[PDB]
Length: 378
Image 1 (tube, helix red, strand yellow):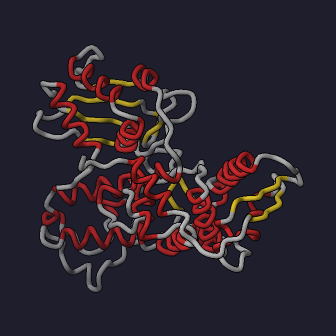
Image 2 (spheres, helix red, strand yellow):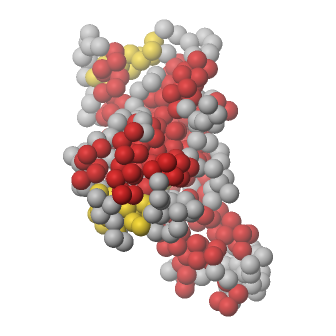
Image 3 (cartoon, rainbow, N blue to C red):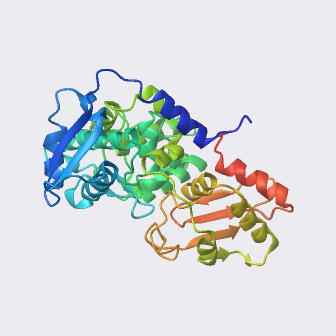
């Protein structure tokens, strides 16, 4: 009973929600479909005080009247999602792993008003979660982490830059001494020569086992959180104008994606037949049987969470698991035999692959599996 429950977190969220003051009866917006994006923007960004946006949504597409408020609302959220999350506009780009999932584009600053647009996006997302509606957008895991104001760590780089991720993993596990590495970008490792110092005089100082974490931190800051800082802060600003920051920290990153993008169920047999196996794992192998038994018995949220750990997101592409993409090119969902039983299973999002040991019992496999889907670090 000391274990996390998503539905409980959700209803608690709801009860804590709807504590507010001086909200009018409704929020009026008249839009034309083709023009929706630029139509919504100046409307929503045009409010005197953000609280108005919390009122029941009254939306009318192209002057159409009388329709069910829920229908027109969810339709609008869908359309406007389709518009915002298109990389065409230059605001967002695709993750290293895998494809459809989005991360912010560091070059979004090309359009000088980009920050305003990010703030707008935050606002409408806030409306989506506030009114209990659904965003069709899906984001890189560190996005959700940054929303919760949580520390960004090496593994989080996995879905940002593959090269950076692998490089920094190697520099983590292996001793940098023999490579004469300094506190500056290394084109040998990172494939780009702009090379500039992370710390003053950095070129002269040598990275060691001692200076490891400092260097990694600086690199992570400069590559990701620094250039993305303004955009993300605008998003969080617009979003927190609706949903309280202290409030949502109830959720971890996965459950948060489940909050914004919603959670559906997942076709099991589909996922099963489209699953590929490695290192001598038959579908008839005992450990595999047990695995799918476990996946079958666990609820929706747990399955989706496992998906989030393996694929890198909660979204299964429409029309099956066969269309599943990862890293560079299309990759099915794969399970590989690795390591000894006392070790926990690991995951690789680039390959959409789950490595698990030959557990000798279904009980053991179960316990280890949930211990994997429930992330408690050590």
